[PDB]
Amino acid sequence: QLTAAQELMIQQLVAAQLQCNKRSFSARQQRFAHFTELAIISVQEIVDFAKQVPGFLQLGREDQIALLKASTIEIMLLETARRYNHETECITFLKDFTYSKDDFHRAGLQVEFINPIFEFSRAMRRLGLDDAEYALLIAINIFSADRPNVQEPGRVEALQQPYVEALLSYTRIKRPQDQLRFPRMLMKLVSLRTLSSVHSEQVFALRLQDKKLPPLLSEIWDV
Ligand SMILES: O=C1C(Cc2ccccc2)=C(NCCCCc2ccccc2)C(=O)N1Cc1ccccc1
Image (cartoon, rainbow, N blue to C red; front, side, top):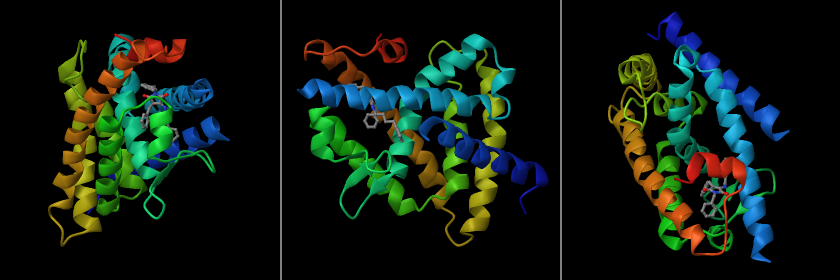
């Protein structure tokens, strides 16, 4: 019962994620450097992906920037959960680039942020999302009309709706017996906002730690 428009929107998102990912990824100062290098790569990958999401380029440049400024850490955390290895309790950012809890801590993050990231990753895992579902959830995250500094929130909201609708229809076919899978996925967007909040506290704490974000991350995350 997916419409052709919905099937095509999903295929575009799944293909763009694959393409963007292929393009982008084909003492304690080293660990912080390495970790921020992954972030700068991902920041680019997300910009590249968002440009492929239908409707995104219909917004004004300032709104495109404002949506990406808020979404980027949340999408990074989605992509982190997607790469969670439950067997050894780690995140496989890249073939071999694996991070455990202590590796996050040695990069500069506190336990108050680390543990919720792993709790979120386990919650995500229990949902058993597929490529279509991740990609739809990322599109829905991007078109959040409530982000700071959005000039056309109505337009954003309107661009979100077909993605929400497609997710609703897709999930109703994937698991006709589990009506509640769809709202539990939307609830992961709630958790991501809190995670984003804690992230901003972690960035703040770098200052009276010993550390400075590199320029490309300072732009998006230092306020
Ligand atoms: O906040 C970050 C994140 C994001 C993040 C993501 C996941 C968990 C925790 C944090 C960084 N790096 C990882 C990016 C991974 C991007 C990515 C995803 C998926 C696949 C490949 C690649 C990072 O350097 N900083 C700055 C920072 C701020 C405060 C204290 C220290 C450092």
